[PDB]
Amino acid sequence: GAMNSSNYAELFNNDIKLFVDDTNVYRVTVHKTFEGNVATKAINGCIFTLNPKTGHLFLKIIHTSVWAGQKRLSQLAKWKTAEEVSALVRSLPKEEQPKQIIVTRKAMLDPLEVHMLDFPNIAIRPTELRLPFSAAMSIDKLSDVVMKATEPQMVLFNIYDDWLDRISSYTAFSRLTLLLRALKTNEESAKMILLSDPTITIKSYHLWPSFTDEQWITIESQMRDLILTEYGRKYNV
Amino acid sequence: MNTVPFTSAPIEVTIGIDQYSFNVKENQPFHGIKDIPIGHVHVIHFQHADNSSMRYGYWFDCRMGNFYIQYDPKDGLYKMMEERDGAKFENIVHNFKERQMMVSYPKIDEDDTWYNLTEFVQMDKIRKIVRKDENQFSYVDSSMTTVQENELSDPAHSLNYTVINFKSREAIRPGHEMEDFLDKSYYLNTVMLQGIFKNSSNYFGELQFAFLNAMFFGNYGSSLQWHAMIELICSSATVPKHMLDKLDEILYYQIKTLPEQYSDILLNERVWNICLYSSFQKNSLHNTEKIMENKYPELL
Ligand SMILES: CC[C@H]1CCCCN1C(=O)CSCC#N
């Protein structure tokens, strides 16, 4: 069934599963034509396919050429996403294929279900959680590789850097979702918190800074404050 | 004109013949139904006055033999049987006509309703959906399940309708995933019409039989099958113009004959709002759209 606060720990059990988010697949700037009409111009996007237990991120870059001469692109994007996720699964060894795929938006269910008909035993599930994965393009190295791509490309990351050497998957996912929720609600302030102290760096092979355990507690607290604030600023509380 | 007679009516029952029905009291002197139009299938159906659980009945074609009904006190139902002796049957039948113990199949001559509801329904196709080959006629009741229902339990008693499944390998060509899911023309035209049904007449015969079983017996699986067959056409961009015209007439007479008080249950909102207003054929069902709007604007 659907994934929610009640069955939340199921994410970190030993059944392989992937989250699929499609909110950055079809990206456009909306601008004016010389005639004063409005036109869109696409930019590169990406599918965000994430193993929440291991941190492994399959970032499929969606190059603007895929949209050339196509109609109803918002609908196409969902089917393109499902085609690429199906292709990913087929590329994995059998023992690496997921038993469940959880889509972050319910409109991906039928597209993915239809592309996965060859995999009757892989459950396609929605979720009632409002996950902040749209903010993945606020992570500088992920945004840089998408915008620079000149062709379709799959890039692999561990979205948890080396955190699993010191914390559990549950704690790592909570940290990730807090960071992403902050970047989503006020990207500029979130980035200021992360990169303020000149002494803490991002390793070349990592996405986030090299915080000690104590610094991570301070960072996490500062991110909570930002989120509550904006919730006040937004709601006037 | 042909006759489906009865040995007697030992229990109070409402007896239907096609779209007609009459009440018969316990041990009332009822010996059957005469003047039944030759040329069409028919259905004779029953609802006991004391246990409205189980509507049941029999599809038959008077051309395929002489068929009568006797109440079985052990199994508790009116059973159809096929006599193999002529003369005695006609002589008792003459006598039955002579004592005027029979109701007349009461067809208004202006009225084409039954033809229009059974236009493509043939006993041969009924007998393949309802498997019981030692009888020329076919029993159906409210509770029988379909093959597809059983997949998701007694096979001998199943309705073997053609399985339609829009998220299935049969329906979706590898590499045309989006194309085939949003435009079912290849499932309709190549898979089902050319491949399984062979022609649109056999497609329409099954659609019509499914509707009739849903209406007369409350058969839930038949209602699902009726709507699935409609949806496959309404969700295809490419349908022969003659099928679209005929489908409009088919559905018109089904919606016309449906009791007004049964619309809540036998009609599926999603299928009809898609077929009439959102689908490829939203503009090709003028007569069906007109009666649904004047008779069931609530559902829409
Ligand atoms: C259906 C009316 C006739 C002819 C068909 C076979 C059985 N019939 C009966 O009436 C059953 S008691 C009279 C005797 N025998």
Image (cartoon, grey):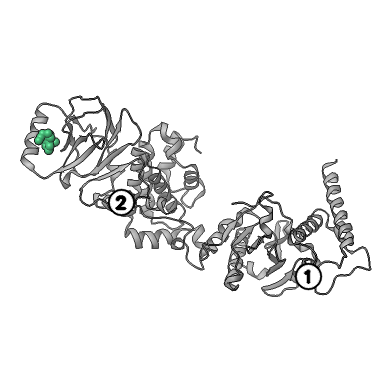
Q: Is A68 placed left or right of A199 in the picture?
A: left
The percent coordinates of residue B100 (x first, y second) are 13, 26
Q: Quadrant of ligand 1?
A: top left
Question: Is B50 placed above or below B278 here?
Answer: above
Question: Is B4 placed above or below B201 here?
Answer: above
The residue wearing badge 1 is A144
Name the residue at 47% across, 63% down: B172
Question: Is B60 placed above or below A34 here?
Answer: above
- Please tell me in which quadrant of the rendered image residue A192 appears: bottom right
Element assignment for label 1: helix
Element assignment for label 2: helix
The percent coordinates of residue A12 (x first, y second) are 69, 60
Q: Is residue A175 visible?
A: yes
Judge by depth and name the residue closer to the eye, B94 or B283.
B94
- Please tell me in which quadrant of the rendered image residue B93 appears: top left
Judge by depth and name the residue closer to the eye, B121 or A191.
A191
- Residue type at the position of mark 2: Ala
Foreground mark, 2 or 1? 2
- Residue type at the position of mark 1: Asp
| Chain at tag 2 | B
The percent coordinates of residue A10 (x first, y second) are 66, 56
Looking at the rendered image, the quarter that the C terminus of chain A falls into is top right
Q: Is B234 placed left or right of B14 in the picture?
A: right
For residue B156, which numbered disc appears in the image? 2
| Chain at tag 1 | A
